[PDB]
Length: 306
Length: 252
Ligand SMILES: CCC(CC)c1cc(N[C@H]2CC[C@H](N)C2)n2nccc2n1
Image (cartoon, each protein chain N blue to C red):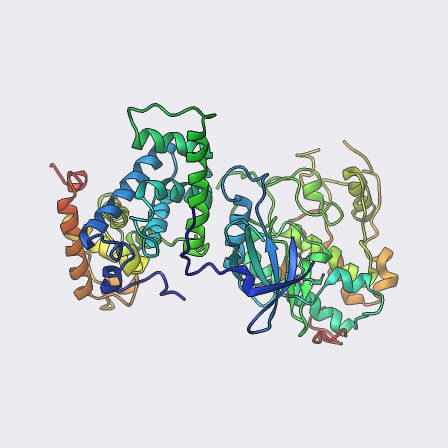
């Protein structure tokens, strides 16, 4: 019936809803701190409390790090006369997609470098705990008032551990930011699907534009096959253990196409090391973090887009 | 914190079950009984022992907040499983958990119709309590168990097929028969389980050549005063638990 007894669950109404990003902005009615609240659950959910929730909830609790959005707590509603259960996050001023689409806020290479260092370290941490993100897009990169980069939408995030051949989720990520392995239906993949995404998001700092917009899945495969060339056992050893399709007679042009918008020699390379077909030949986070785009002048600077 | 779900002996004395007129010893029996159900139910569902243990921990924490007069052992346990299943990644259909729950508790009675309001309610009650136990625990669902620390520790002190799996069994039983889950940390519990398993399997482990005893490598907050205090508590309750020690008793 009721419970009227709960020490570690809060009532959400302590936070005061303002506006929606079911994701609200909010403020605590005593401390006056800004938070974001995320509703859950539905009539669709006809098999106990959502497990997908419990996955996300459990992940957010596990992940605590500079550049990974914080779950403050999970507050709950009262008996039905808002409703359900809410996930409380430290509010993050701006996302990345909004700052790019926004023509005003323009960054220095100095400011652009740091952004990445926060992200890739962010990825480093989450992968370190054996949790894939599986949804790398510009809108999922949050940034604070101080200028602290965070990551969002760990709804899709899954715990991983490669033992035998394992069976991971097939169609994940946004289709634009989706990588090759996934577009052939790879179901035993690992972190560097994200590290791909990061590359798409990195270039998107300059292009200010989703760099690949494949409507069909082979339209996606086509736009990428312009970049990497033909899909070869040459470039990707044993690419022919899966998948005829199209556009397997191209030639490469990673840097040269987007070169006019980077200008930086060091950066062009970093993009191209993330944007490879083979995941075994797709630069890991550490390799990038220790790369000499991060240790070159002008060096990374703190955010102050204003 | 790391001391929220941990308690003194007098903290256990003044549990919610007490203030609703239920004895200290009677409560333990209310608890011990929830495990046996969780265990039996768990076996019929083919879920892990882990899942079953994790289900027992939720209930052990749960009745530190709620009272058994308020919520029955039998109404909570199928929820604690259904959840623990999903938590530990062996999700069971809600229909499935209800079948089992029913035939356990009501063996003669064949299950009601799946259309009847009877069933559809005993459906809801479960969904209800799942939500309630999430709130009670504050969605703190990840459980470290004393087994993890044993399995490592046994290898790291080359234990036999015997002493190792005996030690594992002691831990499994340190959840059913006692409130060691609520008082002491998993690593401490692990040592108790091995220290008894040794005295029982008549094999006191050699100390390392440094000079540190074996238990010092598992958790440094441990001492022989404490192990010999606790192992005795657990041995006794096992002595009382019928044909329990027979499962680990050597007939040769
Ligand atoms: C895709 C946006 C996701 C939705 C889950 C988001 C957005 C914000 N903040 C917004 C405010 C305005 C900018 N679009 C970023 N926050 N803040 C904490 C958590 C969180 N999550």
